[PDB]
Length: 14
Image 1 (spheres, one colour):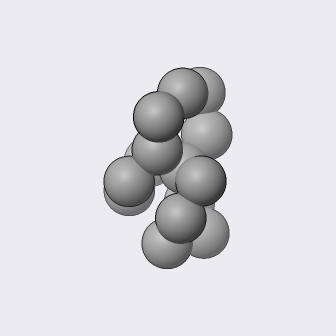
Image 2 (cartoon, one colour):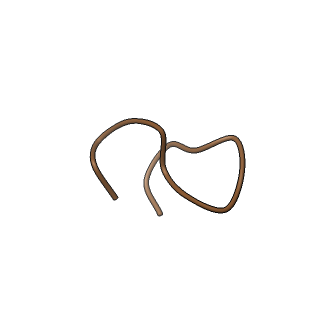
């Protein structure tokens, strides 16, 4: 969980 805004990283893949 890199840089998300929720339950999955929306950036940096995961």
